[PDB]
Image (cartoon, coloured by chain):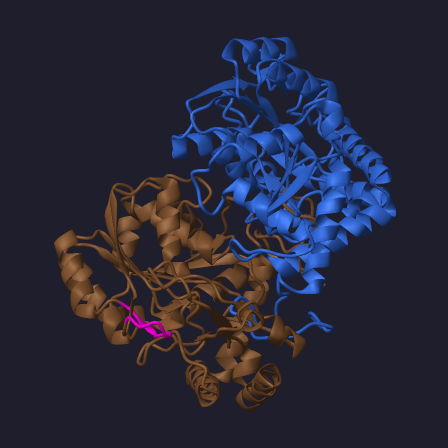
Chain colours: A brown, B blue
């Protein structure tokens, strides 16, 4: 079942129930993962860090921000996460946080937009930021940064000798080409857009990023980004290496999910992601439910809306109608005290290959909730 | 296939291909994992940290050693790992390393024993160690610490107000009862003895350990042991919580492996582990191949032997005979320059329920290698 053409398992790292990282079968998995990930994101290297997306975030911070000044575009809870990483660690020299702003300050609920690009750009040059962190899609607010916004951040941080880190964990199938946009570190995970089991943080790197990872030293043995890149390279060179045990069978499932997506069509999936998001957003606005993300910054894979109902906000009402949603969470952007929301994720090959059904099932549920 | 009685997936954390951590099905998985792990090890709490055994080691160190003096019983590479964690981090006040010693200093190869218990005990009291780290089974040397040795370390560190941390990642089915031995933190993983896929570090805790985790503050957001204990408690209280995404489907496989073991019999498996290890060790000594672990400290789940053959030492000769072994690695204990070894792992339900076959298949291979 597991490694049928392989060797009898007498290593100190596995039993016959798990795929051995030294097997020919896992070597092929790693080579398929690394090549496909580089191609999709246009990256020079792809690093797989056991754990989750957060651990990838932490590996990147700990490798590249030791005694550095950084700037963070905070659009909600998961870009606040950069602050939580840096505050617990106390390893960075400094941190500038540019928070999202409401489009108007009234009692009634107003959507949020990221800090305007001119101000972000100016501040990065004033700061001489070694590293800039920004979420492509912020999961708490449904805010998506445009390709041109990201590019502007890239050029600004490059002009002062720094690198751009983009968190694409909630991007879904909205693929970013790193060289076109000038992104140096791109972070993903297998469980949202890629439709597999959770197991690892994914860190893709540009040439400039690889160069800086090689000339820096991490302060965390387990999450050492340079050491995990060394492991990746042993597989790229036709062999294997060990630092800490990799989630081998879960990574093989991820490789299969990548190829399933590939056979469908990455561009078809990109357009599908947008179609679904727009159609779901329309259903909500049609029922008078307003978006927490301002016009022009509305993410397709995550839709966050305002509510005044606790059973909508905590998700219980949708659960009664047979749907699992995500409870609203704070933004940590100075949002008002009455801030109350609910969240929907529209990730996955099965949703994207049946857009009509995914919308219809959401509609019936929303109708039952509002009835 | 995945959560057939559950809700339609519209959360921001999963697709329909993975088990949602908020589902009733995963709640039951967590409750089975936590109760069975506490029972097996006689622990007050069980914490599951996404990643691997190493990450559990790191979470423990980062929670409990900030500005503390610690003592480490170094028996090989994986207890050197404690030093590697502390050196990269630079968060501990101090570290005393007591390395294993050869039974005699001759040109020919001699086995290794841990530092004698009287000296370990004396040093801990001199040091006033806040934390003592020791490997139950050291994977590089095949050295196993006796239950009475561990107990001695416990009493010594308790007498000066500290806690005992035992790494049981290579213990196999040689179960340790924490209250009997006075162990405060016991670290495991699902992929060696427990016969599942890799995905997480397992940290079991005594009452005194829980009390110290609650009154300390970690320096690493992702591996914060107190924060992962808080997550465990939400499941124990009948709900769920999120810090970073858990490897949900892999943990369900682990729960199933725990129950498979349970149905066979944990004591039957303990005796089986010893039978296999002793029988495999006998086959080696019968062919003149000597053990790297000294008499009385020979581990059953990991057998490390001396060789002068590079094809035995790197494992290629066993691979020719159809077996995957582990290449010999250094100890970092001041071993001689000519130190050359090879390693066998005897982990797993399938080996332990067919001891005759596991020995016989190893014998045929060893015979082919030596022919």
What residue is at 48 percent from the left and 88 percent from the top? A287
Query: Front-most of A104 and B63?
Result: A104
Image coords of residue A163 (percent x, y): 24, 57
Image coords of residue B13 (percent x, y): 53, 66
Query: Front-most of B293 and B174?
Result: B174
Q: Determine which quarter of the picture holds residue B296.
A: top right
- Is A24 a magenta residue? no
Give left or right: position of A298 versus B349.
Answer: left
Magenta-tinted stretch: A105-114
Q: Is residue B112 above or below residue A34?
A: above
Count of labels in the image = 0
Task: Assign the N terminus of chain B to one quadrant of the image.
Answer: bottom right
Q: Determine which quarter of the picture holds residue B99.
A: top right
- Is A113 a magenta residue? yes
Note whether residue B137 is visible.
no
Query: Front-most of B190 and B229?
Result: B229
Q: Main secondary structure of the magenta part?
A: loop
Q: Is residue B68 above or below residue A55?
A: above
| Residue at the extreme front of the image, as rendered | A107
Q: Is residue B63 above or below residue B7?
A: above
Q: Determine which quarter of the picture holds residue B140.
A: top right
Image coords of residue A280 (percent x, y): 48, 85
Task: Assign the C terminus of chain B to one quadrant of the image.
Answer: top right
Note whether residue B20 is visible.
yes
Image coords of residue B363 (percent x, y): 77, 40
What residue is at 47 percent from the left and 42 percent from the top? A222
Give left or right: position of B55 versus B290.
Answer: left
């Amino acid at each position: 079942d597991i490694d049928p053409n392989g060797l009898l398992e007498y290593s100190v790292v596995y039993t016959d129930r798990a795929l051995n990282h030294m097997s020919k079968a896992f070597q092929e998995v790693m080579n398929d993962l690394l090549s496909n990930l580089k191609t999709v994101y246009n990256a020079e290297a792809a690093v797989i860090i056991p754990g989750s997306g957060t651990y990838g975030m932490e590996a990147v911070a700990r490798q590249l921000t030791i005694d550095e000044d950084c700037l963070i575009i905070r659009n909600g809870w998961f870009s606040y996460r950069w602050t939580q990483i840096l505050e617990k660690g106390k390893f960075a020299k400094s941190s500038t946080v540019l928070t999202a702003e409401r489009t108007e300050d009234t009692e009634a609920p107003k959507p949020f937009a990221p800090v305007d690009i001119e101000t972000a750009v100016a501040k990065i040059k004033e700061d001489k930021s070694a590293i800039v962190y920004a979420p492509h899609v912020e999961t708490s607010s449904g805010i998506i940064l445009s390709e041109e916004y990201i590019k502007a951040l890239s050029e600004a941080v490059h002009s002062v000798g720094g690198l751009l880190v983009i968190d694409c964990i909630a991007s879904g199938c909205v693929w970013l080409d790193m060289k076109e946009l000038g992104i140096d570190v791109l972070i993903s995970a297998p469980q949202k857009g890629w439709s597999s089991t959770p197991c690892a943080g994914l860190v893709m790197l540009s040439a400039a990023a690889i160069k800086k990872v090689e000339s820096t030293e991490s302060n965390c043995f387990s999450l050492d980004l340079k050491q995990w890149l060394t492991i990746m390279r042993a597989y790229e060179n036709g062999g294997h290496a060990y630092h800490a045990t990799m989630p081998t069978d879960s990574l093989r499932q991820f490789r299969d999910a990548i190829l399933e997506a590939k056979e469908i069509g990455f561009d078809i999936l990109r357009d599908a992601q947008w179609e679904l998001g727009n159609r779901v957003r329309k259903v909500l606005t049609d029922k008078g439910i307003e978006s927490v993300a301002a016009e022009g910054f509305e993410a397709p894979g995550v839709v966050v809306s305002y509510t005044e109902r606790d059973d909508m906000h905590k998700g219980s009402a949708f659960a009664e109608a047979g749907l699992q949603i995500a409870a609203g969470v704070p933004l940590k952007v100075g949002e008002p005290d009455n801030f109350k929301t609910f969240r929907l994720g529209l990730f996955g090959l099965d949703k994207l290959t049946d857009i009509d059904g995914t919308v219809e099932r959401f509609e019936k549920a929303l109708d039952e909730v509002l009835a």
